[PDB]
């Protein structure tokens, strides 16, 4: 296949933004045609069969050490592309004039409302990133004790540095792989925002997390999804550049909006909401605009960090393609195909 | 005007093809009521509806006066229903599958999907005239099958069949399932077309869950709309269907995913749907058998109800019920109203 040569033309910056958008529209139509079935009997069977298949998998992929480059993101680059809180997950846009910074805070206040956060609670933020929600909650609720968990040394350093600058004493960051983490502490409220996208066996994941929920505590999960069907990211045909270009070697899963309803052995659902794909679509447009508005500094950051002009171009191109393609994907059919699912769980 | 039309109905004065036309109007209004322009709104409607059920009684307690709306004479059921008297849909392999075959196909599908193994203890909640109770008891002679009904005539019929068939592995308990208490547990529990009598599914599943033995399974079949749930409230002042078909006290049309929100005490193991073509085809067969035997049906109803007029009223009711619901379940190739089967384990 000449997928390899198309990918090399992408990596050298030879493929226009509109061509990328058009390529993604084709990929979207292929995936929708693959996933939709003529009868509900078949549609449901496909989802239940998929859910059952996850129950025999590992909780998550062991990331190859050689693929560290695909996971570490330079902080100066995130300061440019992301909003002020470095949220690595969608914002909430009240309209198309909402700013990226506003969208981050709007969404995090929505999390606090839907997760029923109250001052004084113990809070666990699983996969806390650069601390957008951990620091949001810790600043808002000075009586809360907030614990964040991340497997990234540089993320933990950044958050503890922010705690110093913001004079917060109510934040702890644990450096651990959440899939191996052993604790007997229970928490009043647990957040798992954009963490499920790293997992495969949701059953094993939620079993482990359920042991960390206190009596009468709650677990709030946000996952991006397709409205109807779930799938592993595998090439649809011999022409599939998307799966090869965007994702690392290991196999990951696109959830559906209902799939966690089938994983209620150890937690049970209190509430379940969705938000339109328009919100992530707008977010990725703002990420791309910020990248382009600061392209000279982005180049200097990546040339410095990655060690050559060629490899820098490859990674700048990757992030631009990622924003372009996923802005297009989430926009599909006025935001009613790919979207966001939020689930509130109680223990047992 | 609706009360006038209903009185026209109860006397038998409007033909069949326009009963379908009127139901198609009703269908279009319900679908327009239920569907929302966004998934956010559609889901919120379902979650809100599910929460509303948790503020209700488990089931309406049935009064003295209204026994006429629930007692169905056995000779009539022998005419209308298939050979097992299944009062729930059959499975049609094609449109030439007979009513009798559809009953057995569907009950073998229940046995497959509920993972019945010979020797298990089996509980059949709301067993009716015993279609599944007697099917399982004869197919799996090492099983002990217990059926629960609140109907004396149903219990009497089943026990008569056990005598005729020399079945020694069946027990029928005459009890209100919503009040029943026992220390016995069961490897397999069936609830086929029972939750359509329930409102607070959370209380219902909480009670049933205590009856599930270690590593046992509960199998629920409910008719439903694919997407949204609703109470049988009239849609406007031109809705005759809701007033005509349903008794006082409100019942619930479930949605295909609604029991996924009721997993406090049981956990979903599997979940299937079958299209509305199956119940649609079954109601057509019920209607055909009624019509082909109408003089005998008149004889049975005149004896039981006491007059030609009242017999005609109840005959008309059953015909309209079959016509209207064959039309309803056929909507959009059976992709609106349909059947949901859910397999639960104890949580
Ligand atoms: N096994 C694992 N253990 C711990 N953290 C993990 C992990 N797999 C992924 N993560 C972390 O999960 C996060 C997903 S990105 C989202 C971060 C944050 N929830 C936000 O919304 O901004 C990243 O911080 C990643 O480092
Ligand atoms: N509270 C209650 N206690 C016991 N039986 C009940 C009940 N409410 C309804 N039922 C019974 O539940 C049945 C619903 S009809 C279904 C009968 C059988 N499952 C079949 O598929 O043929 C009726 O037999 C009715 O008598
Ligand atoms: C649905 O909206 C979004 C979907 C995905 C994202 C980014 C996505 N999730 C977090 C982990 C993660 C990690 C990645 O590698 C470090 C990554 O590479 C593109 C992408 C992602 C961000 C989103 O909003 C900003
Ligand atoms: C979806 O397919 C069906 C739907 C409803 C039915 C009939 C419905 N369910 C059982 C209890 C029941 C009891 C009734 O009165 C005692 C009744 O009167 C119409 C109707 C019903 C029968 C069905 O198939 C035969
Ligand atoms: C769990 O979600 C993800 C986790 C990791 C990744 C890998 C991705 N991380 C950012 C940088 C980068 C650069 C690449 O090559 C320049 C590349 O090539 C494959 C992949 C990546 C993607 C994810 O979802 C899209
Ligand atoms: C639980 O599901 C049901 C239970 C009971 C009923 C009531 C119904 N039973 C059969 C005979 C009959 C006759 C009537 O008037 C001649 C009548 O008028 C309203 C209603 C009925 C309907 C149900 O679902 C449609």
Image: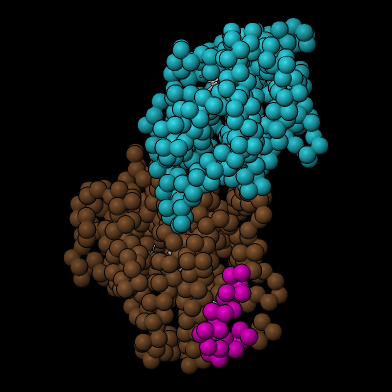
Chain colours: A cyan, B brown
**Which quarter of the rendering shows the C terminus of chain B?**
top left
Residue lying at 62% horizontally and 9% vertically, measured from the top left: A305
**Which quarter of the rendering shows the N terminus of chain B?**
bottom right
Residue lying at 24% horizontally and 66% vertically, measured from the top left: B162
Q: Is residue B172 above or below residue A241?
A: below
**Residue B312 visible, this orientation:** yes
Residue lying at 51% horizontally and 33% vertically, measured from the top left: A242
Residue lying at 51% horizontally and 13% vertically, measured from the top left: A68
Give the percent coordinates (x, y) of residue A301. Answer: 67, 11
Report the front residue among A164 and A23: A23
**Residue A122 visible, this orientation:** no
Report the front residue among A34 and B152: A34
Position of B321 with respect to B120 (left or right) is right
Residue A199 lies in the magenta-colored region = no
Q: Is residue B211 above or below residue B134?
A: above
Q: Is residue A158 above or below residue B329?
A: above
Position of B32 with respect to A101 (left or right) is left
Give the percent coordinates (x, y) of residue B117. Answer: 25, 48
Residue B12 lies in the magenta-colored region = yes
Give the percent coordinates (x, y) of residue B234. Answer: 65, 70
Q: Is residue B237 above or below residue B140?
A: below
Magenta stretch, residue numbers: B5-28
Report the front residue among B310 and B38: B38
Q: Give the quarter of the image for residue A115.
A: top right
**Residue furthest out toward the right:** A97
Give the percent coordinates (x, y) of residue A64. Answer: 44, 15
**Prevalent SS, magenta region:** helix
């Amino acid at each position: 296949e000449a997928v390899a040569n198309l990918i090399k033309r992408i990596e050298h910056g030879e493929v226009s933004d509109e061509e990328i958008r058009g390529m993604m529209k084709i990929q979207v139509q292929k995936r929708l045609k693959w996933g939709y079935k003529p009868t509900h009997e078949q549609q449901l069977a496909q989802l239940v069969t998929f859910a059952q298949s996850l129950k025999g998998m590992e909780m998550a992929e062991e990331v190859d050490t050689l693929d560290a480059e695909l996971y570490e993101i330079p902080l100066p680059f995130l300061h440019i592309m992301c909003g002020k809180t470095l949220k690595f997950s969608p914002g909430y846009f009240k309209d198309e004039s909402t700013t990226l910074d506003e969208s981050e805070v709007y969404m995090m206040d929505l999390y606090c409302e839907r997760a029923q956060i109250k001052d004084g609670q113990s809070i666990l933020d699983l996969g806390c990133g650069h601390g957008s929600l951990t620091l949001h909650v810790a600043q808002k609720y000075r009586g809360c004790k907030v614990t964040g968990i991340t497997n990234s040394v540089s993320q933990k350093e950044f958050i503890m540095d922010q705690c110093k600058k913001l004079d917060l004493s109510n934040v702890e960051i644990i450096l651990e792989d959440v899939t191996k983490f052993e604790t007997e502490i229970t928490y009043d409220r647990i957040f798992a925002v954009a963490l499920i996208e790293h997992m495969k066996n949701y059953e094993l994941f939620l079993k482990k997390v359920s042991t960390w929920i206190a009596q009468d505590g709650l677990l709030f999960v946000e996952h991006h999804c397709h409205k109807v069907f779930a799938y592993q990211y595998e090439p649809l045909d011999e022409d599939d550049w998307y799966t090869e270009y965007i994702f690392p070697s290991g196999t990951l899963v696109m959830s559906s909006s209902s799939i966690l309803l089938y994983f209620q052995e150890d937690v049970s659902v209190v509430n379940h909401w969705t938000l339109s794909g328009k919100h992530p679509s707008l977010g990725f447009k703002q990420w791309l605009k910020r990248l382009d508005d600061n392209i000279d500094e982005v180049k200097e950051i990546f040339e410095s960090f990655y060690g050559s002009k060629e490899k820098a171009m490859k990674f700048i191109t990757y992030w631009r393609v990622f924003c372009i393609a996923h802005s297009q994907m989430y926009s599909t059919n006025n935001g009613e195909e790919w979207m966001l699912s939020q689930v509130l769980f109680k223990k047992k």
